[PDB]
Each structure stands twice: as structure tokens, then as C-alpha cells.
Length: 148
Ligand SMILES: COC(c1ccccc1)(c1ccccc1)[C@H](Oc1nc(C)cc(-c2ccc(C)c(N)c2)n1)C(=O)O
Image (cartoon, rainbow, N blue to C red; front, side, top):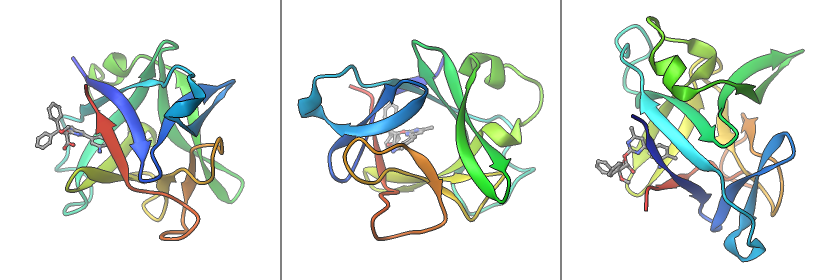
């Protein structure tokens, strides 16, 4: 079964679904935060080493998984109608859906396995969760998983 919880960034902005995209908002908004599901992939040895544990990352209600797809010259973060359990239950590592989770204390960064120069990031209030190649400024790449 997967690990579940909410995700916030260092500005205390929680992931929430707004239409067809994930956005990051303060908990003051009183919107239901997405319940994120995370599960470690059974096949780490086949990928890059020393970059953190490769995980599948999805949401419950609606049951969707995050993946990385090249849209022209840009890797983009997308949601696909997919049950995280189906991916974990697949016999091979499904690379577009995988992210290296690199832990530093209470927070972790999420690096695309398909696009290693890009990381999952949030930015300003109510802005979408995207893939970024730009670190340490306007983009927030350190996230906390709150299992409750
Ligand atoms: C809550 O603490 C945990 C934990 C405790 C109890 C139950 C479940 C998890 C833990 C576990 C062992 C030592 C220290 C801490 C947590 O484990 C964990 N495991 C996986 C596979 C992924 C993620 C994860 C994904 C995405 C993001 C963004 C962040 N931040 C973390 N987290 C962790 O390391 O934070």
C-alpha cells in the first residue's frame, strides 16, 4: 500500500488540485489539499545511483499519477488517469512516472528520472506545480510529506 499525506513547500503552501493542474496554496484557503500517494519503485539498480530513492508519485480522488513528458523543448509535469498501485504493480520501472527523492532532513527534492536537470517546483501563491531547471530563487524545490 502507498505512503499517503499532504505536501507543503517551505512557504507553508500545500498542494491542491485546481481544475486539471496541481497548485500550491496556504492552508488559510480552506480548500481540500490533495492526498498524495508515494511508493518506492522495486528496481533502483537500473537507474542513476547517489541521487535518492526512485519513487512513483500520485494523487487519490481523483486517482491520477504525475509523469514527465517533453512538450517541444520543454519537459512538463503532467497528470494521467492512473492508479499508483497499477504502476507499482507493473513488472518494470516506468521511467516517465519516476522521480528520485533526495532527502535532507524533514524535506526532500523530487528530480525527474526521465529529465534529471528538472525538479518538481512550486512558486508564488496559487501558482502551478511545474518542472523547473532553475533552482534556489523564485522556485521552491524542497517539499515536506505530511503523513498525519
Ligand atoms: C515522514 O517521515 C518518513 C515516514 C515516516 C513514517 C511513515 C512514512 C514515512 C520517514 C521515514 C523514515 C525515516 C525518516 C522519515 C518519510 O518517508 C518517506 N518515504 C518515502 C518512500 C518517500 C517520502 C517522501 C516523498 C516525497 C516528499 C516530498 C518527501 N518529503 C518525502 N518520505 C520521510 O523521509 O520524510
